[PDB]
Amino acid sequence: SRYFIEFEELQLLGKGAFGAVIKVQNKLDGCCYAVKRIPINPASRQFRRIKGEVTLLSRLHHENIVRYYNAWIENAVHYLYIQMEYCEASTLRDTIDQGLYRDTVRLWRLFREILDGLAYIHEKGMIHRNLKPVNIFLDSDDHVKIGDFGLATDHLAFSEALYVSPEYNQKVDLFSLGIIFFEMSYHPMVTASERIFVLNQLRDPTSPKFPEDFDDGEHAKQKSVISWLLNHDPAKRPTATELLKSELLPPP
Ligand SMILES: COc1ncc(Cl)cc1S(=O)(=O)Nc1ccc(F)c(C#Cc2cnc(N)nc2)c1F
Image (cartoon, helix red, strand yellow):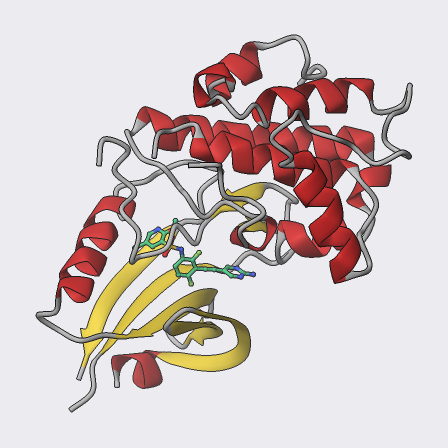
């Protein structure tokens, strides 16, 4: 009703667990937005947790977080709509798959912005827990916007499987970022078999094992950073701030 009156639909962006993300245009302001539509059971524990994650994520304000506009409910069927910024340059996934790894200046900047975003999220006492390239978006100016926290997951620090830590502390996101930065640093992995094996070989308990064509004079710094992020022991991963301040990262 409000969704159909105020917006025009343009494009399916995604399908999650129980919901869709639709690219829409607002009739009044003429701007494109991404709207997530979640069918919801009102008065269920699932719902009341979702409403909590909405109150919590609505309070995030950072240049590297997808910008939040609006949340509302519509009516023997119920929908939750969440209106966010539409990011014109799609996902980090598309950018990795399109040969990001050959642009060392660019991928070092994008890595830094992801860190900016994680540092802010961690400073606010929150954890993403679902960090992966399809959940990092790129705006028209090629800046990182993190989103898709997941409304059914607790993001309060104090309370697909290839990005998940052996384990819930702040340090789960930084393990994930170690997998992500390897994919940013390495050639697009055409096949599923290559993807799963190469990444399972990083996540190997007995120290991260890199492919034969990464053990190079070229990818020395990148190797250090990832090895640090991918430590089995969470207490031995750096904080986003600790890494940001490190002189492993090239100049901004
Ligand atoms: C900061 O995140 C939040 N903040 C506050 C709250 Cl209330 C919820 C969240 S959320 O974590 O549920 N994210 C979320 C929710 C809804 C969405 F439509 C999107 C999107 C997108 C998108 C996809 N493709 C392209 N190209 N551009 C943009 C999203 F990311």
